[PDB]
Amino acid sequence: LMGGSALSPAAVISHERAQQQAIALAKEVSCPMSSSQEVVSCLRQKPANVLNDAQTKLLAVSGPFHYWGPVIDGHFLREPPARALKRSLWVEVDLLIGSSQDDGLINRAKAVKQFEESRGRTSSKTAFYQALQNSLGGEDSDARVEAAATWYYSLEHSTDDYASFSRALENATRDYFII
Amino acid sequence: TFATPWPDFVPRAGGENYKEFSELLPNRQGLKKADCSFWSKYISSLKTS
Ligand SMILES: *[C@@H]1O[C@H](CO)[C@@H](O)[C@H](O)[C@H]1NC(C)=O
């Protein structure tokens, strides 16, 4: 496993987010919102370019919990993995694991910025960092942890420059999503 | 010309100088700036909120 875990806090998005994230998708293109069988029955015949347009309009903000990802299902995941890593013993597989130092979620969104620079949205960068800062605490965005951790990496200078604010944000996400 | 020239405590970033009473009497810069940002900036937001 290179630069990743089975315990990182985006590996299992939940029904509160995954159902919301497709509701957020159907608002972008002119698709009807009726039920589960109608938010798929437009998308089962969309062209493959305009549906990947609606990913870039949506993933450029809202951060890592609003990424698309795995969901707990009863035939594939009995439990979220923090408990389920202790619920699976007596299986033998060696582990060679490790991250890089360059693995930032700005760096994992380098190709996301390119289409945002193409049409041109300078507000899709300053809204991206705070939405990443919104995700910097818990999954429920508790202020008691978000104000606690924003002291420890010392990034309360989102005022004039993006020199120290853009670097120390990458410091903070990498030591909670990666390492 | 008796010891090292003491610089005054400039109350600003890039300053806050002091004197360490050792054999050479050197000029350090910033005492416990990690820990006096802990009790003064972290907890001062935790106590009021
Ligand atoms: C990020 O981490 C590195 C680790 O060596 C550290 O040197 C650097 O100062 C950190 N970035 C910021 C902006 O503090």
Image: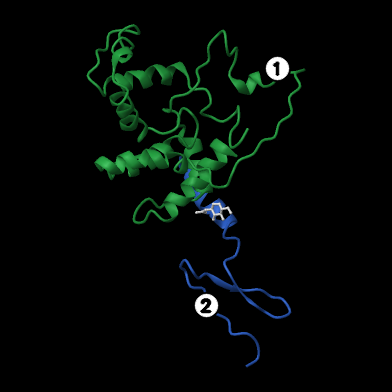
Chain colours: A green, B blue
Q: Tell me, yes or no, if residue A156 can be seen here.
A: no
- The numbered dot on residue B10 is none
Q: Which residue is mark 1?
A: A88
Crowding near the residue tagged with mark 1, few <14, some 14–19, many ≥20 C-alpha atoms within 10 Å = few
- Count how many numbered circles sit on residues in the image: 2
Q: Which residue is mark 2?
A: B8
Label 2 beta carbon less than 8 Å to ligand 1: no
Find the distance from the CA under tag 2 to the CA under tag 1.
63 Å
Q: Nearer the viewer, residue B44 or A87?
A: A87
- Rendered view: A48 above or below A147: above
| Dot 2: element | loop
Report the residue at 72% width, 76% height from top: B22
Mark 2 belongs to which amino acid? Answer: Asp
Label 2 and label 1 in one chain: no
Q: Tell me, yes or no, if residue B7 can be seen here.
A: yes
Report the residue at 33% width, 30% height from top: A58
Report the residue at 27% width, 12% height from top: A33
